[PDB]
Image: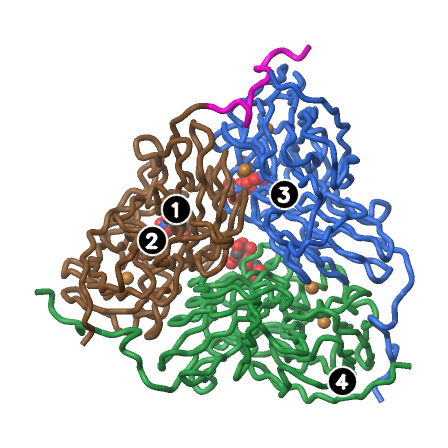
Chain colours: A green, B blue, C brown
Amino acid sequence: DLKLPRQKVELVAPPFVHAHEQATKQGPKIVEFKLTIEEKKVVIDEKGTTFQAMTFNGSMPGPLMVVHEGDYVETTLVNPATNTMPHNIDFHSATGALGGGALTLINPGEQVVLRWKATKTGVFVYHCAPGGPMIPWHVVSGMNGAVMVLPRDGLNDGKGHALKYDKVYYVGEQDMYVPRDEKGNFKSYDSPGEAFTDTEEMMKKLIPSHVVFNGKVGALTGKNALTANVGENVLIVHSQANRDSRPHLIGGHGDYVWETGKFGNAPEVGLETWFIRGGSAGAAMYKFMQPGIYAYVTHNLIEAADLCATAHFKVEGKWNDDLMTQVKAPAEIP
Amino acid sequence: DLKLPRQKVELVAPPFVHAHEQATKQGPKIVEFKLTIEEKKVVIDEKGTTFQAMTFNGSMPGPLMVVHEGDYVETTLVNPATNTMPHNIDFHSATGALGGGALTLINPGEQVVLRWKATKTGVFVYHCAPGGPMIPWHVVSGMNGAVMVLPRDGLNDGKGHALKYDKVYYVGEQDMYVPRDEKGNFKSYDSPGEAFTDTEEMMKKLIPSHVVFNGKVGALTGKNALTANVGENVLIVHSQANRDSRPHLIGGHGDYVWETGKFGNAPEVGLETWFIRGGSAGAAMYKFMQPGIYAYVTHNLIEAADLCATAHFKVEGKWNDDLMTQVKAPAEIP
Amino acid sequence: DLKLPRQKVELVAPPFVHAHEQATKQGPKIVEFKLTIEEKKVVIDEKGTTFQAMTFNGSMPGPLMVVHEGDYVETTLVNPATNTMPHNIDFHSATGALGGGALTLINPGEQVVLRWKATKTGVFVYHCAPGGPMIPWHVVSGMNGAVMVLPRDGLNDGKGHALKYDKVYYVGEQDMYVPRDEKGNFKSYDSPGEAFTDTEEMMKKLIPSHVVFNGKVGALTGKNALTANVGENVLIVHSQANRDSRPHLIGGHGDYVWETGKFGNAPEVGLETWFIRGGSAGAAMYKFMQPGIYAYVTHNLIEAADLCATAHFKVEGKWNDDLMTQVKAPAEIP
Ligand SMILES: OC[C@H]1O[C@@](CO)(O[C@H]2O[C@H](CO)[C@@H](O)[C@H](O)[C@H]2O)[C@@H](O)[C@@H]1O
Ligand SMILES: OC[C@H]1O[C@@](CO)(O[C@H]2O[C@H](CO)[C@@H](O)[C@H](O)[C@H]2O)[C@@H](O)[C@@H]1O
Ligand SMILES: OC[C@H]1O[C@@](CO)(O[C@H]2O[C@H](CO)[C@@H](O)[C@H](O)[C@H]2O)[C@@H](O)[C@@H]1O
Ligand SMILES: O=N[O-]
Ligand SMILES: O=N[O-]
Ligand SMILES: O=N[O-]
Ligand SMILES: [Cu+2]
Ligand SMILES: [Cu+2]
Ligand SMILES: [Cu+2]
Ligand SMILES: [Cu+2]
Ligand SMILES: [Cu+2]
Ligand SMILES: [Cu+2]
């Protein structure tokens, strides 16, 4: 019926993003992705707290899918028989059937193939939504990711100038709700199913126990720090599927920021901190001007410092004293 | 003194909106509204929880008032003798006297008439504000609604194109604070007055027990689902008088969105989720492309699924397979 | 090395702002500021609750620093020997070294001098950030202020028209976390150090006990009410270093509002309520049209009325009946 070229995509684990063109002269294609659901218990903090996670492709967040405006996205979703729950998928980028949720419901042992057309550009959340109280449960359990729909001519500043990024990272923020016991220790559970009751009581009080980038406290620090060099223009995509976030690059700015995350609107310029609406993704580009460590955080500093929400960037290059200088090092007050 | 034609308006109960023109060739008029305050106990959930509500015109939210830029809005507010508290009204659309609160204070048995000029276009909250700690109390009790001030030429996209809506619905989101007892059951009270102490202790902890559209869990589902047909351009006005919200049309987008809700600013385009600042209203227009059920939610999915915050839309028309198709129905994993 | 004129600035205590030009024909200068850190116990409410505060220059927020685009800001930070903790400073307006935090760490008895170039216009937060869990602690303790970086040609509406303000006030909103005892009374502590453990447990639950403008409940009411006259264009700068706020001028509007607070973006017009992202500052200008009291609030009315977050404005001039009139004073219902 639909007579167009097919392109397969190997998805990569966040914060990386599969190779793709920014501007392109290709026409619309059918872009094929596979997602496999994995239920598993995982360690979310350095003190060893465990969590019944549910993931697309074994990661939190799910991998980022990149396509251009007009492409058709054909997704195979697989719920292996080792999973215990029905799952589905809804794309905020898609039109109809609750974003696809209503066509994609699959029990363990099943798979489904869905095609939707990419009519709107920007970055959009995808997430599981099986029904009723299960919706919030699967999402705060890790079943959310994002999809970026680029314009064929690539990004622009709204004033006719191309904005080309040299690299792109995907940062998925996850609010997690782990209940404590009488003594105030986090509880461990055998199955997602048994975690459900206690997790649900706690979720309704709306205060997360952990807020983490990429699935774990510290995931994007040390050896897994994001990297750049002075002069590189870096795009950061940030999703939050349930609760608002306020990302900030410490030492840096957002040179161009789509805080609503939709590229038919012109980016704002020069931001210190931006706002990601719960249930959405946004994008911010910055050209690094100085080397050293930067921290990428949500500027609820309690969340940042105390609940897990910090990534590091490690940037190489030449210090610029014109931009910033220590005039006089610490010293006794005269 | 003010020599202009008078127009009376029969207000309708949300989510409907009284008949009005979008663009108009009439000159400024004095538009006359009546609001009567009702204190009453009401059922807010399907398990029968009750709540001491205080309302304009017996509904939550108050009815939506529509007028054009330059009109004079003349409002009669009535506090019948069967009410037990003084009430007033403040319009965010109005200039001076705490938005009118300071001229509109009335005890049970009294009424007052206020006129203000509509100098600013957009959608704006109105709410009771009697004074001190009473302000938050009356608002989270239901005494808030909205008023839409259209431009005489109707809405535009910012790029010179008219945006005409075929219908408009008003969705009022209410954060409610109902205290539990020692056993963890919601408490019932005889009077608003007696609910005050317990409600106040709980309010200060800032976590609502229920978040509802149009006064009740389920109010805008089943028989009272919002409706449209494929091809209709629908405007949704959303108010939140105290706490932020993040509305999302599941299966749909915001084609044009005034998230700050003021029509002197150009709408943003193509949104997945938008943000209604506490103490404000916003507006989003969407042309339906596909039939079926859509859910309108705040994309805090805990609030949506677990605390009451979901409306349904039921849309008639022809499925479009080009936009979205089930390629392969659920099936055993090969 | 850097061969330019030096200008000293005497900082003033908020909500006032040191004298400065809006548009200017001066070239880039080195602008020199001194900040001295003060740890002290202070009264934050009318019932006499005390709080271990940490401040720049003995106030909450820190004073507002004003400079123009291209200036070099040279800041002497002093940590006197009567303080018990190391402190530093990070500017969101600055580029590199965690906004300066990584060059400015000083123990009691020390001082440091830092210079950064003002490449981006807008209003930006500055705050202490010593490291780890200490970051949120020092900030919610009062160690945050703001810096405004004006364009040399002054502010504009985005459509080529100058916007000149007749006065400017700086409103710093502080979320504070004071723990209660078993009986439910606020606790007093001898030292910042001893407050730390209890404050930290409470901070992680993310619900502040007090939200105050300018350091105290009632600080900007009564004798210290902000003032204006009908016809004055007033700029209000609002910072929030950790948690979001939704400012609203009751009786008024935001005629021009930079909600993200960066002047390379055009202001929005006609707002009822705007949003200050946690970790940022914004600015709103309003021309007063009517006399009387206005309240400036965050339109979480619980925060406003119940947790400390209200300022008053007292405006002189002639009432305008065309804008708003009491047609009929309170009276018995016929
Ligand atoms: O030591 C018993 C005493 O402790 C409480 C705590 O309030 O409950 C604990 O002990 C129960 C019975 O031994 C456990 O089942 C319960 O789960 C645990 O919290 C009281 O119930 C009891 O009187
Ligand atoms: O069974 C009595 C025991 O229960 C507590 C709960 O901590 O209080 C309950 O009983 C009181 C006196 O019977 C009631 O007035 C009170 O309101 C109820 O919670 C204890 O106070 C008491 O020791
Ligand atoms: O009256 C003693 C009784 O009260 C509790 C409250 O649960 O604790 C109080 O008394 C303790 C010992 O007297 C204090 O150290 C404690 O800090 C205070 O809360 C119980 O522990 C105790 O059984
Ligand atoms: O200790 N369990 O609730
Ligand atoms: O059970 N009443 O608090
Ligand atoms: O009463 N002190 O926790
Ligand atoms: Cu799932
Ligand atoms: Cu969603
Ligand atoms: Cu009232
Ligand atoms: Cu209000
Ligand atoms: Cu400090
Ligand atoms: Cu910061």
Q: Nearer the viewer, residue B269 or A309?
A: B269
Q: Which kind of residue does numbered mark 3 sit on?
A: Gly
Residue type marked 2 = Ala
C62 w.r.t. C131: above or below: above
Q: Residues within 10 Å of mark 2 (few under 14, many from 20)?
A: some
Between the C-alphas of marks 2 and 1, the distance is: 9 Å
Secondary structure of the residue carrying numbered label 4: strand
Residue C261: x %, y % from top left: 44, 56
User: Camera-side residue: A276 or A286?
Assistant: A286
Q: Which residue is mark 1?
A: C164
Q: Chain of mark 4?
A: A
Same subunit, tags 3 and 4: no
User: Distance of mark 4 from mark 2, alpha carbons?
Assistant: 56 Å
Question: Which residue appears at 63% of the width and 14% of the height?
Answer: B109
The answer to whether residue C326 is magenta is yes
> Nearer the observer, disc 4 or disc 2?
2
